[PDB]
Amino acid sequence: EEASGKEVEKVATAVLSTTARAKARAKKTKKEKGEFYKNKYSSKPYK
Amino acid sequence: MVDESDKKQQTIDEQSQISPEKQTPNKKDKKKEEEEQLSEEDAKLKTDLELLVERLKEDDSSLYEASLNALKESIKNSTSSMTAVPKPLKFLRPTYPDLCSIYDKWTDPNLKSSLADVLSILAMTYSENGKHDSLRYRLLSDVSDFEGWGHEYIRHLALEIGEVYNDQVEKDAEDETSSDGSKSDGSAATSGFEFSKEDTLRLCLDIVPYFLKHNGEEDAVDLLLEIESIDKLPQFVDENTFQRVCQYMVACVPLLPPPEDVAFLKTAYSIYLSQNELTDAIALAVRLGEEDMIRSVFDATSDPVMHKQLAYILAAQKTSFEYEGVQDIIGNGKLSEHFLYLAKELNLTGPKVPEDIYKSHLDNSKSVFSSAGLDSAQQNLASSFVNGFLNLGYCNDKLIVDNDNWVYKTKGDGMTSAVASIGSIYQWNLDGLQQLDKYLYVDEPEVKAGALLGIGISASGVHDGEVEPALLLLQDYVTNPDTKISSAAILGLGIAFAGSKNDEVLGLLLPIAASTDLPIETAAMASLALAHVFVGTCNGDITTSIMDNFLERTAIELKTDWVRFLALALGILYMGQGEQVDDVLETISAIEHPMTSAIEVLVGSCAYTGTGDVLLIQDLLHRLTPKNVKGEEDAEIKSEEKKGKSSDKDATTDGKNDDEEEEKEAGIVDELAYAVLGIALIALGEDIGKEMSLRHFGHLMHYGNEHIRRMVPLAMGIVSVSDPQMKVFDTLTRFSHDADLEVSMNSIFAMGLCGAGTNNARLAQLLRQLASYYSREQDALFITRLAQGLLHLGKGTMTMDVFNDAHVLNKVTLASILTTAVGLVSPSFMLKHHQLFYMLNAGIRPKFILALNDEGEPIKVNVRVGQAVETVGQAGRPKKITGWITQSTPVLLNHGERAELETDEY
């Protein structure tokens, strides 16, 4: 994905948490009231 | 203590010299160890119970804490109170308090939570038998003052209110629900709930709203009626009992869903009805809008006397008060038959007497002409209008008007609004007909339109006694083909009869007067008529109105501005209701456009009107979403879309305005501080959003009817010189009337200073002047306001046209609508029954922000203001009756009611 592509995901994660918490406080109140490093070689042939 | 020999008949006495300690140790051990000894334990229950009574009159904490420590365990945590079951259940009379001694007297947060639950289970079950009721009663009334009894009764009744929760959260209930651990079905609920009501009235006043709201039922308010009416004469006097109630009912309006909210009120009327203060009963009946409620109150007061007296008068003045008119029609009947007088009694029933007091008030305050005279430029438009607006409400404006010169000279569509505002002078007063017929009979159609609006406003005064009624004039004028002339003719009629709905009213407005082939803005006035008449009483959210709402929309949608006007008239129709508005969501939406969905959310805010449990969070998901998605990503066909996007902004502001009106006395104060903040946030997120929010902001103030009215507007108004849009002043001043020439004197002085220094448009100057002249009506003349006055949380009936135009562009054309502003309130007078126009003295209280009172009833201490004053704006409206000094008592209790005062002099 290279540097630019990995970065799109890192940011996306940061963004969801900020947005999450910006609605969370109010909503919540008002909700209720109302395999191996070295596999050597396998027997199993492949083409 | 810890000995098993201490259970002997002999060893009660030997032990008890030291201290009674027979109750726990040995006894407890044997009861929880052998079933055989439960047969013995039963007889000794009585003996034990008494040992708790004695050591409570000699209260000493230490010797409960330590002693009944190990006692806690047997009761319910080990035996679990059900061997063969019957045996522990019967012994719950003397062990329920032993649990409570570690609940209550021993203190620790950790043990308060834990054992609270356990107690709930036990109360409930022993209240099946109904002997837990008996334990409550003997503490409430006690036998001796001690710290015991006074904590114990609080806790027991507190827990019952607790129980109803478990069954709502989950189906499961029982122990798994850890809220009380109780099933909560009859047995210890039904029988206990009935006792519960009686107890909480006597000492208690602060857990009572919690009991009523949690149940969330009108059945609960119905049982409450009976219980309260028993005590209302012996334990306490009617006066004390009646306020205590009035505290409960107001508190529960927040935290109730729509179908429950109204239902709480309906029942509340009944409680009032029996209770001897009939004044309160009648105001709430109108608000509800059910004629039947009004009928009963009026008749009960009238019939028992065959003489005149205080009684006849009292009934008649309460029915006069509404300028909706619904009470007026009804009240004619018994009094009419009697003929003590027709002249006096009939008149005081109807709105004939309010006209007469208005005349009187006009001479007292005068009407100091000080109108702008400016000619030329767009400043010309403004001057002409100001003459109307300055002298809004019943006055004599005849001499200036008599010169038709300036009326005709008023340029453009501005001309129409200059005639409309001549119409505004003539509110609730037959007089002023004379001037109107001149414009109506001559020149452009334009002049005729303002004149016709004017007849509707002049016929308003007297419409029940039907003196030169509205209907006669305007009927002739409907027929006239021209859309402008039809439409105006039918809106004046809508205003006159107001919330009143009759065969005359219904059939006139039924074929709409809007041409569907022309989208004239002053032909929008036809849908306004329908909206007005339906509101000001219960709203059936009728289908006749939807058929036509769709009809104007479909035909022409090219002009976006116009179709927004129809959307807003529909939402407004429904307002005054939040329970049938859900039903009409389906109905409206059946038809398809992106435009029909725009309408959906507007009407949505109206449905959820009651408390901010629903409302505030919808109008916040909505708000955030444009801002948030846009922020995230960064860090004919056209005309439909544009409506869509505009309505979301509107809708967020509207939901906030509608919610705050309802809330707590406490909650109003915090929402206001926040509102100012919210301006910064919207400004951050989106440029476009900021502009719309501002204009609405000043209407936020008017709609909610804030408590304050003196300091805060003016504070805000300085800041909003800097913020764009100058409609912020227009809407803000309709709130800011208060006493006129107190706030408003500062508003005009300030506004013209800033406009002459910083002028950035003649359009900008137009708004600044208009608003400021509007604000004052000379020398505190009866003021416009959203509230009726009689209804504290009252919504407008004729003061809803304001909001419609705030959302859309700023033009001189919109001002025609604004001329309607009927909203005038009576100047109170202390009457006996000889109809005295002169007060002893009456107390006003400006403080209205209190959260100590929930009633919002003015403290009796007050500060004394003279006679022949106007009932001034909010933070002044609470008026209590000074009369205590001359050995006099109000029969008619004013809590800040519009209402004319009446006393019985001892």
Image: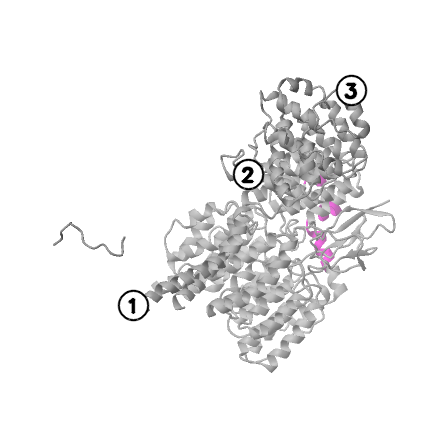
To which chain does the residue with label 3 belong?
B
Which quadrant would the C terminus of chain B be assigned to in this image? top right
Part of the protein shown in magenta: B333-358
How crowded pointer 1 is (Cα within 10 Å; few <14, some 14-19, many 20+) is rated as: few
Badge 1 and badge 2 in a common chain: no
Q: Is residue B230 above or below residue B842?
A: above
Looking at the image, which residue is at 88% across and 50% down?
Answer: B886
The amino acid pointed to by label 1 is Glu
Secondary structure mostly seen in the magenta stretch: helix
Q: What residue is disc 3 on?
A: B10
How far is disc 3 from disc 2 in space, using C-alphas? Answer: 44 Å
x, y percent for residue B159: 63, 37
x, y percent for residue B530: 51, 53
Query: Contact (CB < 8 A) between labels 3 and 2?
Result: no
Q: What element does badge 1 sit on? A: helix
The amino acid pointed to by label 3 is Gln
